[PDB]
Image (cartoon, rainbow over all chains, first blue to last red; front, side, top):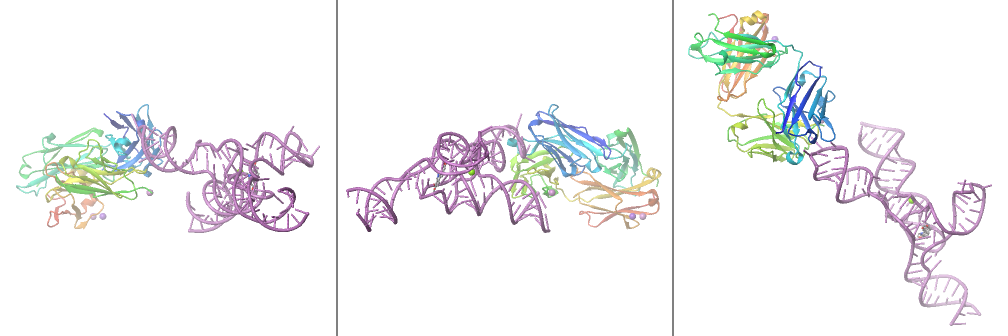
Length: 225
Length: 215
RNA sequence: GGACAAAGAUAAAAACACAACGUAUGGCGAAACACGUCAUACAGAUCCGGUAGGUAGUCCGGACAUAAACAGCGGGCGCUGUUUAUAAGUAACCUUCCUCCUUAGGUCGUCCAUUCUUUGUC
Ligand SMILES: COc1ccc2c(c[n+](C)c3c4cc5c(cc4ccc23)OCO5)c1OC
Ligand SMILES: [K+]
Ligand SMILES: [Mg+2]
Ligand SMILES: [Os+3]
Ligand SMILES: [Os+3]
């Protein structure tokens, strides 16, 4: 019944502003403290801001002091986080959390939102290039071989990778994307197959990057000699 | 001065039915204003314990919290498969609120040696003007492993990016990809490229290499 | 028997009123701060002298203590010094004397002084 839904995230350029919303349901925000906590990709939780009930008192963390403002609009039952002068280190999923009732939950945060992603980067939308990680010609005659696709130089996340239009799903590892110094993302998807099958069976990886409207099907095959 | 919460261990390996303990140490007094949360991948944290001893409504009774001075512990009496996640501690005694760096509780498994493969740059990529050589370490446990790049037996530093998969649902294993990015010209000026791997299950450091422009 | 006088013992003794607005801690209010409310504590009734015979929590003077403001020194904080405050009120009322602050200012007064003992001289 109690729910918090964040919204307003997206991609913003460094030094630009964004305004996040936290719409509440099943409770009135005026009777609770509201918190914003962020999580950078691959990192832990970081408390960002809090607003107290019946006074409006705002408390912020050093990383955001002067550049972030937490506000509440009781008539729309929504909390807000205004971000100015944003920089790359601010890229994260932002949760809003309700602080619990003191009699029932102490000061723990008893309800959270799903989060909303904020990406601070000067990169422009770009479709990936997809290259064949061909199977080793020196592969064992009766041993396992490995083949793959490299999805490279795409912004922003995500991409989806299937193999043989999803028929081949066993033994496939799609790796997490890593942001490279270019500001563009890169990942690789690999599958291990029996080496007896390399000439008989055709392997295709299907890469989709919806943000750029990019669908590519790349066939990976052993190279000459 | 802001309060620091130091959580140990950063990563823990255990099995179903294990008794698990995670600790948090505060730089100052935080009284009992400490809470513990569980976060599973891709999901929001869920409150487990508040006021550092109290079980939050609906959380299973196999979770408990204890306070000794400025040290707080979260204990799971018997692990269950749904209990493998990252756990966080938070102080709310004084603003600004601080959270622990986190502790990930992962399934413990038999030591498995990595299978290492090397993929030379594709010809399409060389037509694009860049070269990437990918080392794959497949289906190994534990996650700790070292990957080193040798170009003509010359160790490369600052040109390699690694990516690791989460633990597999069936193998309870990890996989790692290492990509080495060189210019097409720099790639064209050397002949031998090797991926040297060290792992606990490897009795010697395995090296898988290829020679440029060769079958 | 009485009178005057000194020296003792003993007793007595001042009207009216005397203020938590506020602060601190804690509990509670849908409540980390703010706010509302409740509980508890906090307002120099300290010490010494004097007020002309005596009687002072409140008069007069000094000391100490506590609080605030300000000045200075040292490396928001600490120390030092000075000033002020510590109820309203010895205001108001009654009341004597004095002074052209006279539609005022100061000043005498407002309470108690009981009972008994010794000695000196008529
Ligand atoms: C020698 O001892 C003395 C001397 C003078 C006094 C005194 C006591 N009181 C109460 C008063 C007094 C009381 C008052 C007043 C005036 C007053 C004037 C003088 C005294 O007007 C208001 O009430 C006292 O006893 C210790
Ligand atoms: K170099
Ligand atoms: Mg006085
Ligand atoms: Os600090
Ligand atoms: Os070189």
